[PDB]
Image (cartoon, grey):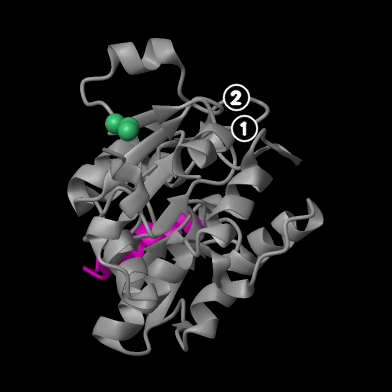
Amino acid sequence: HHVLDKIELFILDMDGTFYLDDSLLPGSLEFLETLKEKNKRFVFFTNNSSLGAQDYVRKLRNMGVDVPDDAVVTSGEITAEHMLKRFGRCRIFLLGTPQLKKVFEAYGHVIDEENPDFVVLGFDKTLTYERLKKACILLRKGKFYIATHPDINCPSKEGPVPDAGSIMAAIEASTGRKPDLIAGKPNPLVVDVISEKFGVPKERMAMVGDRLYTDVKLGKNAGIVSILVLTGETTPEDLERAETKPDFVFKNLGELAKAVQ
Ligand SMILES: [Cl-]
Ligand SMILES: [Cl-]
Ligand code: NI
């Protein structure tokens, strides 16, 4: 034998894996209960930088999942922390929501649209033309260019909606530049960070999610086990079509839980 017994830390997708819309999925609670009993650990991760980790902590709590503050990580905190680590406190032009802006400021970065050294692109649900224009002008001056994550679209109640990667396509068409760094899944940085933060070797970690391409690729890139659940973006028919398969497939977190009980 039982290979999954060795996993000490599970990185979990949120919407589509732990809950769907505003409702918890079958076995989600059971799964956390099991982890607690077995002295194992989890952390939620999302590429979705339109909100901060605390907004998602709040969302979970409001569904009756009591989690500590450090239970969620997003591409926003990964990006802000990586910049802080490698470059110190940075002057940035940010294409991001007010929530993402607080994330960068919490890491001691400063928004300076006049004299930035970085252009930083997130899931900017507050994008305007003028802001796109300014970003392009700066990119043409050769500013260092960072995106929180690559995703072209984001799943939604209304179907696939443009995400950071769609904005990237506009920027690239206008300036000819792609980001110098894209921090989020499937960049293995995410895993390295979490691994160092909680002191767990990659060999005792797994990625559990519903994003066939991204989550599997994160596992390959990072060298950790990928477990796909069937509750979200991925169907059995998608799995059959997939060029690269996950390490394990489970109906949902409740069935995964039974695998490790
Ligand atoms: Cl066996
Ligand atoms: Cl056996
Ligand atoms: Ni057996």
- Does the magenta-highlighted stretch encompass residue 143? yes
Residue 218 in sight in this render: no
Q: What's the mark number on residue 25?
A: none
What's the residue at 29%, 58% (across, down)?
Answer: 204
Could you tell me which secondary element the residue under label 1 belongs to?
loop
Examine the structure image and report whether residue 241 is included in the region drawn in magenta. Answer: no
Which contiguous range is marked in magenta? 131-144
Residue 222's spot in the image, x, y percent?
A: 21, 53
Please state, as top left, top right, bottom left or bottom right, where the N terminus lies in the image.
top left
| Location of mark 2 (residue) | 159
- Looking at the image, which residue is at 32% across and 78% down? 83
Q: In this picture, is 121 found above or below 107? A: above
Residue at 66% across, 65% down: 67
In the picture of the structure, the residue carrying the numbered disc 1 is 156
Three-letter amino acid code at the position of disc 2: Gly
Q: Position of residue 20 (x, y in %)?
A: 67, 35
Q: Secondary structure at mark 2?
A: loop
184 up-or-down from 13: above or below: below
* Magenta region, main secondary structure: helix
